Amino acid sequence: MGQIFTVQELKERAKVFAKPIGASYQGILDQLDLVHQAKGRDQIAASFELNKKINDYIAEHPTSGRNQALTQLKEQVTSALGLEHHHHHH
């Protein structure tokens, strides 16, 4: 809340409705804490990388107002690593 979104705090808002645990999806939360490993302009510059790619979250659930927070919030730090949204044909 001070600056970078906390993983525990995200779970509260991300709780929405009781849903199955992704387990492997938790990687999205490790980015918040991991961002502490990168340093210099590369760390923050990463913030602009996933930023655009995160726009996908809105496209997936644009009807939800929560995406506005996750999109903008994650775009700050989660992107701070530029993990590049993974996708495949299916």
Image (tube, helix red, strand yellow):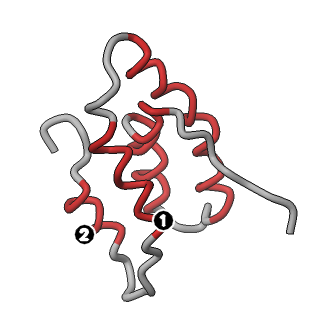
Disc ID at residue 12: 2
Where 58 falls versus 5 (above or below)? below
Query: Percent position (x, y) of residue 65?
Result: 47, 62
Which residue corresponds to mark 1? 25
Q: Amino acid at mark 1?
A: Tyr
Give the image quarter of residue 2: top left
Q: Quadrant of residue 42?
A: top left
At which x and y percent is residue 56? 65, 51
Q: Which quadrant would residue 16 be assigned to in this image?
A: bottom left
Q: Against 89, is 6 above or below?
A: above
**Could you tell me which residue is drawn at 64 percent across and 40 percent down?**
53
Relative to the observer, which residue lies in front, 54 or 63? 54
**Number of numbered discs:** 2
| Residue ID at (21%, 51%) | 6
Depth-wise, is mark 1 or mark 2 nearer the camera? 1
Quadrant location of the C terminus in the rendered image:
bottom right
Q: Earlier in the sequence, mark 1 or mark 2?
A: 2
Near mark 2 (Cα within 10 A), the count class, few <14, some 14-19 or many ≥20, is few
Label placed on residue 62: none
Mark 1 surroundings within 10 Å by alpha-carbon count, few (fewer than 14), some (14 through 19), many (20 or more) = few
Q: Residue pushed farthest right?
A: 89
The outermost residue toward the top is 41
Q: Is residue 13 left or right of residue 59?
A: left
Q: Residue at x 54, y 40 (%)?
A: 83
Residue extending furthest toward the left: 2
Quadrant of the drawing holding the N terminus: top left
Give the left or right position of residue 17, taking residue 8 as reference. Answer: right
Say which element carries label 2.
helix
Q: Amino acid at mark 2?
A: Glu
Residue 31, percent across and down?
38, 45
Identify whether 7 is placed above or below 73: below
